[PDB]
Amino acid sequence: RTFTKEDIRKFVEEENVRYLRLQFTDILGTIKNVEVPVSQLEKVLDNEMMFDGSSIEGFVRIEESDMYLHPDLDTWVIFPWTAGQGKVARLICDVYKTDGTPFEGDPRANLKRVLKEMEDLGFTDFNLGPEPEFFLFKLDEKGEPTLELNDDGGYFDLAPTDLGENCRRDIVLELEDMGFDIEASHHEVAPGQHEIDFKYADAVTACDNIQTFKLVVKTIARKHNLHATFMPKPLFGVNGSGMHFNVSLFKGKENAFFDPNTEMGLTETAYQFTAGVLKNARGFTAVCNPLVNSYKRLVPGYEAPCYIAWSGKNRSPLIRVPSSRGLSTRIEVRSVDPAANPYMALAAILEAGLDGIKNKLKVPEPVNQNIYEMNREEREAVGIQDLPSTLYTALKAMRENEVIKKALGNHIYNQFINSKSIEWDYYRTQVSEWERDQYMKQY
Amino acid sequence: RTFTKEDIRKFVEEENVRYLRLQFTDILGTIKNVEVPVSQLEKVLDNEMMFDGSSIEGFVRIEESDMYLHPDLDTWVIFPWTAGQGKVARLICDVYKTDGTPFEGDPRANLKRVLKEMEDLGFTDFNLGPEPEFFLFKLDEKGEPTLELNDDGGYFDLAPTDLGENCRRDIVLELEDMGFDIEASHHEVAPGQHEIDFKYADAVTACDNIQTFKLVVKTIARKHNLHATFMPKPLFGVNGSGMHFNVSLFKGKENAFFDPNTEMGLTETAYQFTAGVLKNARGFTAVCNPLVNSYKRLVPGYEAPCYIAWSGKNRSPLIRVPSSRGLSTRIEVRSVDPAANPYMALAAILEAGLDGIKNKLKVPEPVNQNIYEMNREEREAVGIQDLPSTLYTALKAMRENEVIKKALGNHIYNQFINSKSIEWDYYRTQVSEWERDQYMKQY
Ligand SMILES: Nc1ncnc2c1ncn2[C@@H]1O[C@H](COP(=O)(O)OP(=O)(O)O)[C@@H](O)[C@H]1O
Ligand SMILES: Nc1ncnc2c1ncn2[C@@H]1O[C@H](COP(=O)(O)OP(=O)(O)O)[C@@H](O)[C@H]1O
Ligand SMILES: C[S@](=O)(CC[C@H](N)C(=O)O)=NP(=O)(O)O
Ligand SMILES: C[S@](=O)(CC[C@H](N)C(=O)O)=NP(=O)(O)O
Ligand SMILES: [Mg+2]
Ligand SMILES: [Mg+2]
Ligand SMILES: [Mg+2]
Ligand SMILES: [Mg+2]
Ligand SMILES: [Mg+2]
Ligand SMILES: [Mg+2]
Ligand SMILES: [Mg+2]
Ligand SMILES: [Mg+2]
Ligand SMILES: [Mg+2]
Ligand SMILES: [Mg+2]
């Protein structure tokens, strides 16, 4: 069910592939890659491809720059928009040190580490169905983006109110040709916003999917004279974009979250799992919402969470339980946004979830109600805690949580905190057009 | 005949449609749809598939916000401007709740509910032939509509006075290749105004016929560098657009409105029905004219109604009985405008008419003169009421009518009152440039 070096060797000759892209993911969720001519295949498969690690965000220092790429052969895919003499294929890679030690800073591998912990606890797969929503801006004279959305449409609109109809069709086409099992395509709430959904996959595969997804969304958009962006809240007073993380544990072909006995079809594994996410949600939101701009979307009134609670069929809370049951039984962690590093965010959610199982915690009361229309002490009554309000308050929540530190390991944890703290302090000393428009004449 | 799943399956295979487009309508009459690839065909046909009802206007709240779609299979249609590999079929859907119940808030479901009460009183089909007039404006360079109209032509004008022949011929062509029975196209009275008529059909498919028609006109208008608008009165001083509702009852392929033996040629069933339409007109005007702007159409001098009355061959009253008889025999409610939600409006007029049959009401006598040149005191004489003049009074007339509260059921009634009252209380507060032009120098 895994591919061998000779599997890959045959694909390269069958489809007459000309170039290889070796791709991997830094600490910011940003995909990086070098292209080699397929004449270098044997170097690729014997794990002898090198790059400057010091030139990558959350990696090594300049005095130990050299690092290697190790291709995960299962990640093979060919880019259905490439020619015959320019056919390009891809391998996603894990990062290693010169000595053959896998890198403590690799985000993909760190998720592979946390998934071995769920396995020793008796679960065969951790499935994630991501929901990355995006905005489409128009490009100008000289190719750079503008602030003019591509339409003034809204949820489930059709053409011409929704003008990214063709562009979404082109993204489904190339994606389907890449082995994506697409599920739905539609205009989202906010003007210019779009959603394309695809079937869930096992943890490592799902993240690889997100990275591919972004990759295809952005380039096809450019071919439609549009600029795509996964920024959390591009604009005040409209819905932001969130990368909902639908998750579930399988004991093999069977969904450990589903109960065919009860009226709400949830097992107590699932209740325990949701318990852990809720307990540790403060500690992991810096990682699921790692930009300053991520907290301009965690504001009430736009179907994004602000308050740690769970409920079914309810889109105001941090955890919605969608109505589907059966193999589709899942918890939806709505706080995640598309700027998150998927590998790290899923590591976060998984180990928080595994915290609830290993510690057999009982879940709080479902908040079956519109949490926005609740006031500070009406929710303080039922024990509903807030998520961090700023990126600075999110990191502090991180420094004091013990689970996110285990889910990330010491390197990523420190490199993440060190970067984002510098990030905050550049922001914190910016003077906004807001401050000037409100304060330059008045005072 | 009536299509069944495997009928659906075979058409999908035999035609290689790659994409389903599932559509439903919100309270404001606006079409809503999601694209899903044919991968998901079986998830569609098992009514297994969902959307967010709190982001549909006039539907559910965010706490209870998960809803499903049941496709009406008889609505299968392949878009004749989608080639292979990008070929889209459509299915109109009904809307269901998480408990498997139809949604009280579905406007289409509702028309179906009322049509059931029509089968009670012994009628097989309620046919409607709609007449959705529209305007075409010129786009500017960056794609947005301007206030320059496409021609300056009149009723029945030719090219080059009429510069919409070519936009209309393309509309007519796509429409026939979607199965429409087109009956005429021509320039309408106002400059830039156009009409395309088509055969009547049963109530549901006719409202479906209107939604498709609207979507196909706006699409093709863009292809021609135009903006189609179904706004009732886009410009002062020249006719508005109406959506004439031509209706009749059938006792099984027999025009129940046609009496072959009498001179006028109407059965007493047709008379009773008009009595009910005429009695309840004020109560259903808000739903037939839901815009502030709807009421700048409903003003004398423009071939559009403003007084509750009925006449044959006569184009001033609310209701006109056109000369044609036989199976063409119909009443024409001329108040309807194209911003009206088709399903709701038809539900409203269907029950008003039913109100008159069941109670065997008797018809006001016809007003066989140009009822725009009758003085308020001359009209009060014969006992002729006025239509509501503002959306606010129309809402007042609606809150005080019992037939309309039962045509919509409480959810649609309540949702529409609420939404439109708010739409008014913004309008009533804005300062018109009319006001600043007459008053700002004089005072
Ligand atoms: N058992 C499961 N575990 C994790 N994700 C799942 C499971 N079943 C379905 N999903 C995922 O949840 C996603 C949610 O799809 P979507 O239609 O976007 O739901 P909504 O938009 O209503 O939250 C799908 O992408 C699917 O792959
Ligand atoms: N029995 C009927 N019931 C409802 N509509 C009908 C019937 N017979 C004809 N019609 C419809 O009336 C419409 C005529 O519109 P049109 O020719 O524009 O009339 P007008 O003379 O009012 O412009 C068509 O949509 C046609 O299908
Ligand atoms: C209507 S929405 O509910 C959009 C939510 C918002 N944009 C956010 O996640 O921040 N999401 P979904 O795809 O789950 O229906
Ligand atoms: C000549 S007109 O009579 C124009 C009516 C106008 N546009 C309105 O109903 O507002 N309508 P029709 O197509 O029924 O002849
Ligand atoms: Mg070697
Ligand atoms: Mg291709
Ligand atoms: Mg979704
Ligand atoms: Mg969404
Ligand atoms: Mg979601
Ligand atoms: Mg199923
Ligand atoms: Mg006509
Ligand atoms: Mg007309
Ligand atoms: Mg007419
Ligand atoms: Mg008789």
Image (cartoon, coloured by chain):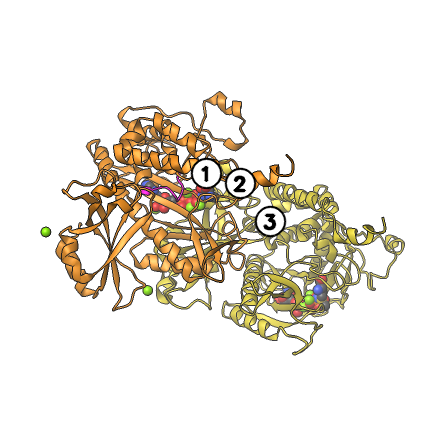
Chain colours: A orange, B yellow
Disc 1 marks a residue whose amino acid type is Tyr
Q: Position of residue B80 (x, y in %)?
A: 46, 68
Q: Which residues are magenta?
A: A333-342
Marks 2 and 3 in Cβ contact (< 8 Å)? no
Q: Position of residue A217 (x, y in %)?
A: 38, 54
Task: Nearest to the eye among marks 1 and 3: give it.
Answer: 1
Q: Which residue is mark 2?
A: A432
Secondary structure character of the magenta stretch overall: loop
- Characterize the local packing of mark 3: few (<14), some (14-19) or many (20 or more) Cα atoms within 10 angstroms: some
Disc 3 marks a residue whose amino acid type is Glu
The alpha-carbon separation of the residues under discs 2 and 3 comes to 62 Å
Residue B67 lies, with reference to residue A409, above or below; the image says below
Q: Earlier in the sequence, mark 2 or mark 1?
A: 1
Disc 2 marks a residue whose amino acid type is Ser
Q: Is residue A104 left or right of residue A384?
A: left
Q: Position of residue A376 (x, y in %)?
A: 52, 25
The alpha-carbon separation of the residues under discs 1 and 3 comes to 65 Å
Residue A120 lies in the magenta stretch: no
Residue A213 versus residue B241: which sits nearer the camera?
Answer: A213
Q: Is residue B25 visible?
A: yes
Q: Which residue is mark 3?
A: B117
Residue A234 versus residue A127: which sits nearer the camera?
Answer: A234
Residue B88 lies, with reference to residue A112, above or below; the image says below
Residue B148 versus residue B251: which sits nearer the camera?
Answer: B148
Q: Helix, strand or loop at disc 2? A: loop
Q: Which residue is mark 1?
A: A427
The alpha-carbon separation of the residues under discs 2 and 1 comes to 10 Å
